[PDB]
Amino acid sequence: GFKQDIATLRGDLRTYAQDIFLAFLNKYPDEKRNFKNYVGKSDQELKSMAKFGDHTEKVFNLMMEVADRATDCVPLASDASTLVQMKQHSGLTTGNFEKLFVALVEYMRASGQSFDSQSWDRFGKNLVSALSSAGMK
Ligand code: MH0
Ligand SMILES: Oc1ccc(Br)cc1
């Protein structure tokens, strides 16, 4: 289930973080407007860029902590307010997060592995709800 999937993802997190974020950027190319340095690059070129690997991993490192702290795929309101208040998220709306979790769920469905894709779908919805409650537009 969800808790084991957090362990699976942490067991290879760099490669999952990069592959899911690439899935997101390829499915939603307009999302590169927040990553202007990632424009005009192939997947392999992005995987050569120090901040692509470093920032994506740190994003997924915190996503896994938020997932681990959740009850029944419902994140803590403290985690939601943190994600809202971060300066690096000043521009964002809940729609950006919805799209990421759509890409994460689709990655999981297409994988060879017994990921609890339904739990991740709930988590993404619960996280968007929590972000809205904590004041993200
Ligand atoms: C596609 C929009 C978007 C979404 C969705 C998003 C969702 C999330 N975020 Fe987060 N985040 C987004 C856009 C950014 C930006 C633009 C930056 C700052 C610039 C950059 O390239 O790192 C950022 N996020 C930066 C970060 C960093 C700092 C990276 C660093 O210092 O290297 C963390 C930890 C982070 N986020 C957390 C998270 C978590 C957890 C989620 C849960 C999915
Ligand atoms: O640097 C970043 C990588 C992935 C996401 Br999602 C957000 C920021």
Image (cartoon, rainbow, N blue to C red):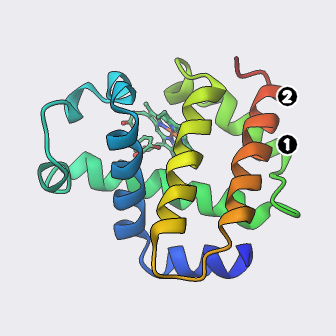
> Which residue is at the far front?
110
Instruction: Tell me the quadrant of the picture where the N terminus can be found.
Output: bottom right
Residue 55 locus on image (x, y percent): 37, 48
The answer to whether 46 is drawn above or below residue 128 in the figure is below
Q: SS at mark 2?
A: helix
The answer to whether 29 is drawn above or below residue 127 in the figure is above
As drawn, the label of residue 133 is 2
Q: SS at mark 1?
A: helix
Residue at (68%, 60%) from the top-left corner? 120
Residue assigned mark 1: 77
Residue 137 locus on image (x, y percent): 70, 17
Residue type for callout 2: Ser
Quadrant of the rendered image holding ligand 2: top left
Answer yes or no: do the residues labelled 2 and 1 have beta carbons within 8 Å?
A: yes
Mark 2, Cα crowd under 10 Å, few <14 / some 14-19 / many 20+, is: some
Residue at (54%, 38%) from the top-left corner? 99
Q: CA distance from mark 2 to mark 1?
A: 8 Å
Residue at (63%, 76%) from the top-left corner? 5
Residue 19 locus on image (x, y percent): 35, 60
136 or 50, nearer to the observer:
136
Residue type for callout 1: Ala
| 2 or 1: mark nearer the eye | 2
